[PDB]
Image (tube, rainbow, N blue to C red; front, side):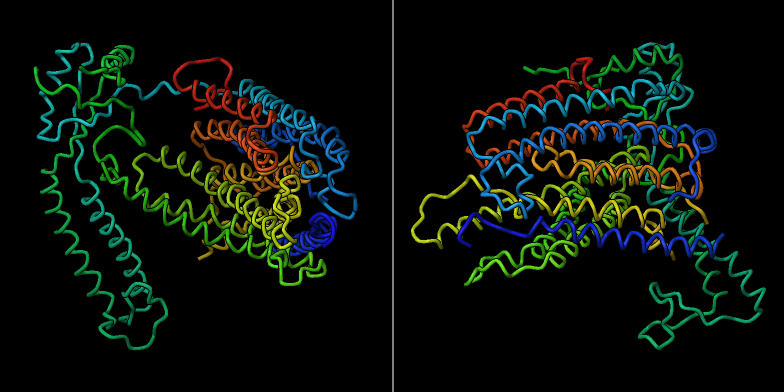
Length: 619
């Protein structure tokens, strides 16, 4: 190629931007047609959404308003200082028809402006924390004080005789009189049978209606996944409805009866104990171990662990998935299967953004096409990144959590973390390694050049698979979000709540990409800010005019706060990584970035034990 390594002209941004703009307008046209069939911006309101849809929605929109303010400050600062700074360097022998001029790759190793880059990263962390401190600390509802009157204990499974438990608690202090000490059972099996039974009665009701309307016996398929199999199947004879449900309901009824009779057995020692005067209940909790052990009735004392469970309530008939005690294996197997699917979903993105760049036996620069290697790969990646939340929620449901608040929180975090691995982590790591082995092959194929020119090593196109990604996200994702597709295309087979966890995770994946690649690719911040403004408008409209108000758990917004604090940490980590991969580990800039990261991680993990009054209020 006779000069430093080249790629697309301009990074292939204008073509994908124009085509996404055209497709975004097309999707707006289609949505307008469908809306006119049913019944700039059509309207915007403030106090109506303030009052109608509830404090939860107001809180969420306040979150995204604060993050748009954060990205405006970010964008001005970056595109004002860093972009001229990065463009001032002259490592890339200037062509000016290339993306790499704006990036961090256009900066010679040993230059002191890397200090400016890392200083900006640190200030970015500080300013994000400050902005969302101003958010969460000005409109924050307090903690609950209602149900703190009972304990959830992994107690004795021998027989869990309740009055002996009350006698023990009398020994401790008799003030907290125990109205009942109810141990749970294999309600899993019992109301699995009972839920199949209830399905049977609803089915019998609809069958009563069906053969009261038609008044004719029906030739119906009971075989699952036999919705429209009118052909003869081996051993799949279709029985008349009446004889079907009558025998099924009778069998399930007697099975449920005997099942409950043996549910009298099956201790599963997890008994609840109702208390009084929550303060003394707090004393009782303080009485128990917080793992404050060093080592070296008058019976077992170490096995009880205290907690406050009640999802509906702390009474009998508690819950269903309270089965697995040591079956983490379910959780890890589900995570591993999803992770393998995740690799197989990320791989096409890379091996479609880099087919032409594989150094062919005659590597001339006229083997490219910006459209095919930019717009299609990021469109594929965005399609997968809009399909992931559904899969993650499905898998989380099949993990069998046993606290619905816990399930929602952990599902939100899993959705965000898997989006991070599939959008930011794996593509960036893969592209960095891929370009390392590109430079190796190039500098080896050139005759006997032993020294590997680490100065000009970075992502192929110096990082433009993400500007295209964020642009495609913004346009062809807000168009779809306004179209209600992210749930309709999957559960089309009547109005619904919209899950907060999914929106938080998706908005956080995009914001994490944008804030991770501010310093090392300044041109990206305006595109992310445009994305987030359009997301704000579309969320406001969709939330107000087409969805249902409800009452979500408080701890979710704490999760959003934690995630926002997390993203600039990733920014620091990848600035460290690229400094290491460019200019060696021992270099002073890499040292100072590394020590900043270590200070940040130690102070972040210092909050769980000590209260340092500086971290942003969250989990």
